Image (spheres, coloured by chain):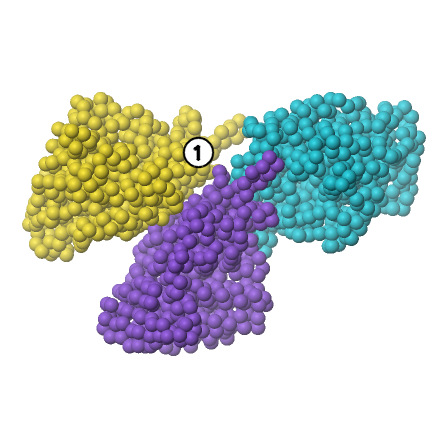
Chain colours: A cyan, B purple, C yellow
Amino acid sequence: NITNVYGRDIRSLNGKWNAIIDLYDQGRGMKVYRNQSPKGNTDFYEYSFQGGLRLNVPGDWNSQTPELKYYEGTVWYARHFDAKRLTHKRQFLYFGAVSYRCRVYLNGAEIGSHEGGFTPFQIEVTDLLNEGENFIAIEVNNRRTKDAIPAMSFDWWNYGGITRDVLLVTTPQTYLEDYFIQLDKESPNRMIAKVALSDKKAGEKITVSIPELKTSIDMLTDAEGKAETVFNIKKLERWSSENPKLYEVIVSSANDRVEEQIGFRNITVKGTDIYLNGKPTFMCSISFHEEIPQRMGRAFSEADAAMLLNEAKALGVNMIRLAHYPQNEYTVRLAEKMGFILWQEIPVWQGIDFTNNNTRKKAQRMLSEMIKRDQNRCAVGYWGIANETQPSKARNEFLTSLLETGKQLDTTRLYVAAFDLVRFNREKKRFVMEDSFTSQLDVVAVNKYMGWYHPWPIEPENAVWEVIPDKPLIISEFGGEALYGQSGDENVASSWSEEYQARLYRDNIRMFDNIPNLRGVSPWILFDFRSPFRFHPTNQDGWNRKGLVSDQGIRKKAWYLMREYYKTK
Amino acid sequence: QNITNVYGRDIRSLNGKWNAIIDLYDQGRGMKVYRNQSPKGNTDFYEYSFQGGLRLNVPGDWNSQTPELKYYEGTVWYARHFDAKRLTHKRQFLYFGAVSYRCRVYLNGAEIGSHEGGFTPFQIEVTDLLNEGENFIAIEVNNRRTKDAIPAMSFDWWNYGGITRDVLLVTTPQTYLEDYFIQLDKESPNRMIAKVALSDKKAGEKITVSIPELKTSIDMLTDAEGKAETVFNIKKLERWSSENPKLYEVIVSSANDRVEEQIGFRNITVKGTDIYLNGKPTFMCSISFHEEIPQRMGRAFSEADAAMLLNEAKALGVNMIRLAHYPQNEYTVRLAEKMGFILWQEIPVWQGIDFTNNNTRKKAQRMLSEMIKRDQNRCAVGYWGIANETQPSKARNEFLTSLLETGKQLDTTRLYVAAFDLVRFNREKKRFVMEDSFTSQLDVVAVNKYMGWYHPWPIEPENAVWEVIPDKPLIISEFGGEALYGQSGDENVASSWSEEYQARLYRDNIRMFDNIPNLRGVSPWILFDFRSPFRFHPTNQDGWNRKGLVSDQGIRKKAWYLMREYYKTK
Amino acid sequence: QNITNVYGRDIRSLNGKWNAIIDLYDQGRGMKVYRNQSPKGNTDFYEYSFQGGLRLNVPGDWNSQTPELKYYEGTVWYARHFDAKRLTHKRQFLYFGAVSYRCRVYLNGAEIGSHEGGFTPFQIEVTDLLNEGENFIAIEVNNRRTKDAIPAMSFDWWNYGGITRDVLLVTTPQTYLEDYFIQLDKESPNRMIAKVALSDKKAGEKITVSIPELKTSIDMLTDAEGKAETVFNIKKLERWSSENPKLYEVIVSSANDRVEEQIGFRNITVKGTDIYLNGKPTFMCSISFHEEIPQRMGRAFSEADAAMLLNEAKALGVNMIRLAHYPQNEYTVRLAEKMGFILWQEIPVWQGIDFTNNNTRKKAQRMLSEMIKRDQNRCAVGYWGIANETQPSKARNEFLTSLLETGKQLDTTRLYVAAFDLVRFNREKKRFVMEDSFTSQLDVVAVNKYMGWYHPWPIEPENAVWEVIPDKPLIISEFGGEALYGQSGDENVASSWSEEYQARLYRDNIRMFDNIPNLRGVSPWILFDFRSPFRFHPTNQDGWNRKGLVSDQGIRKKAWYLMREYYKTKF
């Protein structure tokens, strides 16, 4: 899979695609991908890709027409386009994300497939493009199954469709495939530069430039085409939230050449303190889903990133948890430019089947797609392997096999997981937790909703945690629900009132001091978002109302409290 | 198990606007939303409510009520309050004409019943479970397609979910008339079977059947199983016929119970390759329609719906109605009886079904039994259908054979049929023939062929001769082709979706029908355009199988008049 | 003006899916979308097309076809292609059964006609205007409410716009029978009338009316105006009635033209406080319904629609149907005639419109003639109604009387009626009463009164005694109250919207009908729930006037049965 796809020679295939809603999964059996028209006087075809529904690409389909809102199943996307077959350079179809599973058909024939709706994938078509007009037809499916990631239930909407850019990539016949150019784990001056080619020949040479620095390394490929060196770097200005430093890095070779803006930093841990570069940093975070609430559909563009991140800005955060799945690159790249530390996880959690090994491979596969795509993102200071799980036999293996997979790819960043297992034993009047697996981590994250799902069992001021005192602690989810505009009694949870929410936030803030290892907090969540089991007809109406901003973009009373808390660090 | 003639009992309707929650990821059951919990403390809260939100009409599909529900598959929760009086003396039941496709019924916070299969009724006794005054009922209605269901993952009609027919409160005395079967013995123009059964199993209770119009009253007594049975003879009896549809006031009575019903009487028989209605050989001028009202894109459920569907069939001139691929509601059926239509009712078994699944054989057997038992006193029915087209196989033929065994143990007065798409043209005999030995155990053999449409004409229509099961009566139960109403196109081009092509196609099949010696009925597929999720052509189909002789808007196509004229010569 | 019996001519449907453009700002005419200009080359570009997007079904209202159109008021452009042969011998017309409310028609690039009023037909001859083969027709359809229209700014039903009835191309020979009127004379049970006209204002030409079943045939010839006419005796005549609705085959021949039609024959007469039908004094067990299919939220237009509406009325036990406040479509009327419903049909004038606008009087008159013209031969139409409830004044009395004159010139076989809501309880007399001199001019007086709904009971029902117009026959043309099917409530609480309250209402009103000496007809408002934009109650109404005996979903309410049992006691 080709890294830094946006530095390459790309033609976008976004726009209006013809579509067929295929509820009974009959289109394949009818070979709709051939796009047949009646030839004679006796033949006919009960479908067509002209003059009917057209869906916007990129996007979810659910927000595009009200009939599609709850649609699960197969939708056929199709499109004509123009290619030119090339003597010299090769060509690939590239997909940012297709939710959830798909089959790609170019000119009447299956050419590839993929599963997992948040990670990119590509198919080569150098020897497949007809010259001039081509016909591309994709069957996108989002049916929930017990063996998927995520599985049958999850607290967000099952958006289907081609949810990110469709790109035609052109590369020279022997191109730079992957590279990994980042600053060493614990040391601030030692630089790694792993690079790989497309062809596998020894003796080809690879060179890494940084012209702002006065640095330029050469290396020779091995038989597998890969090159790996480690070297010293000089007047190096490390990326931070304060100044988001990104240099212009250049990789070149025989006949390929990529430019990427890349930054460098050390993030590590000893004891219960998290060190960005030199200084120990407190993580003043926020999460949000990949979703623009005002149009009730997936976020997919540069403009969408501006809106989501420019609100995280005004709230004054230094970190961002990208919810529960890898989000798109416009968001990730724009957060790196602006200064947010990033945490990015795969949608693994208790609802996954830890029995099934095919799902363990899917998990390891998705983790790798995540780590690979964003391996050069100094903003990403965390990799998440799971949200709330419970300690079991298959669980501990499953997750350890995920750190196994991940660590074989990148040990610069940290491996966190979230837990919902803080409990209140009465005898000691404090909040404990006992889970053996927590040792294998770097940071530990707790999801707890004090004064929402968990009624305060003692005064906040006095409520103290003894949860895993050895490693640092991030509260990755807390908060509660409120409908913007709804007033009510600040002592009544079910009022769904900005008053009660703001008081839930007051009580929680006063609880944070009562634990010594908190090195960050993150409210769930920045914006109200769509979830299919938020059934309350007048309070929820399909929305998880825990956001600090309502589905209409307007800040709740709790938001201004969190602004003030973050201003003081 | 099931109370016959429900609309002759002490009934109150629970129809109306029920409160509704769409439950896409099926979380409602675990949250126990059927408990109807309201917050009462300062730390309480529930993420559901059955007040202030979506309300769905009952009865009806949900698909046509809101555009978000048009393609909705999954669970929808229906709920409402109702008042009831806990009657010291009597018994009270809940009765569902149909809930599609599967459901769990909860009353006052407690599960009390379930059902699978979306076209047949079922009931739950609630005598001991009702509060006095306000009661609350929640129903988990689900329509997810599964491999083991009937139908299964794919079928040529829309997957309408909901409480599609009446919800009834039935009051009966503590010992009530549970069931009765009163029809002419077959063949026999004036012998009357009368099987009757009480609810308690008690010996020697009196039971009376009267037909005051025929000055007949007949007394009997229960056997240990509370069942009674008598044959008797009857004179000056008019027999129900498609020509004049006579029906009789019939009264069943016990010590405490009594129920009235309009029942007619007839004999339908086969001899060789002919079908005999009340002695006279008769040719079945037939049509089908789905249980659907095309102008609103929803299921049909009322007396008014019945009239609209059935008066369009009367206007065509037909004497028979094939009720699609499933039993339809009691309104449509009893209005057809009143208006003199012969009825064919089948269960949605076809090739798609999983025949290697014993529970699926049992599910088919229970559906065919619910169908037969509900309509056993409807003299208008002369054909129990057991399957649409199915390919031979050991697993299939044991299956279908077990459908015949199940029916005959309930009913022998009506004909049994199944439909077959195994008609083939070999160039050798220059004929149309069919290789299937299951046909031996059918009374009538139905065939679905679409010449000039799915299967284009190899030989000229006037030269198309048929050698299909030539020792039995043969009915073409499906044929036709598609047309968008109003669209003019070239008479010769099938893909034109023109009315003019569909007329010519119907012209040609009229020819073919004269070359078919054992042919004793035809039946266009279909009366109205209907909804189907794999008819994708954006501009000619848009979700419609345009094979109707009438448009989705209810305008008659060119081909409709040809069939009216074919049907006047009969 | 309008060719009689369009459905018995040489006709050709133009129904089916047309392409549409929603013209919110009425910028369509300014850019001449009716020319269907496609771009020529690099310079040309056009901001409109008539293929590729939205298609509206014809016939129908646009409101029920897409939710974006439910409330839409403005111009919608309908257009389509169609083929045609130019026949020099024969002539050809476009016939619109109804376009609501107003429209301009645009053949092949230029306007060719217009019409105003959305419940009655019109037509345009096109003979010398058709191309050969491809013809293009665009229709600018508009439903903006106005102060000077009939109806005007407010009315108690949905403002359905669009091409709501059939659209036909009709062929007739160059000279044809443009019109005929053939009905028994008023009062007399065996003498028939037989008027005919022709396109050519030509003397001498001969017409031959004849009805095979009664072995009776008559010849006649035209005056200089083309209009023949005679009266004649006819024998063994079976007359049309509710119990036995005899229609007859009627053939009429000219030189080059011949038309058949089912027509029956009956006598409708008022003598005293009594309505007489074929001499028989008869009580009108009536009901009304709008031209609407509730489950679909749309106008009716087809035979299927008609059968659903009329089989629900037959089930209830009625001999009469009041077709609500406007003339309805020819399918409904004609099938009602075949089933045996006496029909009352009226125009939508009532207190709302501007009686001081002589121009609006002209519209009212042109609309009453169109209604009377189209359905001249419908022996089941027993009543023309000129107005729903209106209140006395100089301009009103003038406005109404002129309509009575307009009509009585065109027809005197049927009763004329109007509705009134002026019945007050006089506390002194303890009686229900009305004074209104204009009533004397009517054959029958209709009253709208909602005792126990709009007007709470001032006296116990069995003591409600009417002395309303003691000398004319009285018909209570509207009464009733609202209920939401399924909703339980206190039978004493009218805001409960409960079937229980609406049944009590109906029992109480039934009881009052025993106390009205000149009562010769009752007629519930209404059969089905129907749409109206000021029935606002969010959970009781939701845009439904809930006064139907049958819900918007087609299920009978508890009141439906009391009226059934009431009608069985009137036979």
Which residue occupies the foreground of this view, B424 or B305? B305
Direction right: furthest residue: A232
**For the image shown, how many numbered marks are present on the structure?**
1
Which residue occupies the foreground of this view, A138 or A254? A138
Q: Residue A11: image x %, image y %?
A: 69, 36
Image side of residue B109 versus residue B510, left or right: right
Residue C174, by quadrant, is top left
Which residue occupies the foreground of this view, C167 or C414? C414
Vertical position of residue C315 compared to residue C425: above or below = below
Which residue occupies the foreground of this view, A61 or C449? C449
Q: Quadrant of the N terminus of chain A?
A: top right
Q: Is residue A327 visible?
A: no
Q: Chain of mark 1?
A: C
> Residue at horizontal 64%, vertical 47%?
A153
Q: Is residue B307 visible?
A: yes
| Pointer 1 local density, CA inside 10 Å: few below 14, some 14–19, many at least 20 | many
The kind of residue on which mark 1 rests is Ile
Residue C142, by quadrant, is top left
Q: Which residue is the site of mark 1?
A: C21
Q: Residue B102: image x %, image y %?
A: 52, 56
> Residue at horizontal 53%, vertical 54%?
B111
> Residue at horizontal 84%, vertical 32%?
A273
Q: Quadrant of the C terminus of chain A?
A: top right
Q: Element type at marker 1?
A: strand
Image side of residue C309 versus residue A43, left or right: left
> Residue at horizontal 23%, vertical 49%?
C566
Q: Residue A306: image x %, image y %?
A: 67, 27
Q: Residue B280: image x %, image y %?
A: 30, 73
Vertical position of residue B198 compared to residue C93: above or below = below
Image side of residue A423 versus residue A159, left or right: right
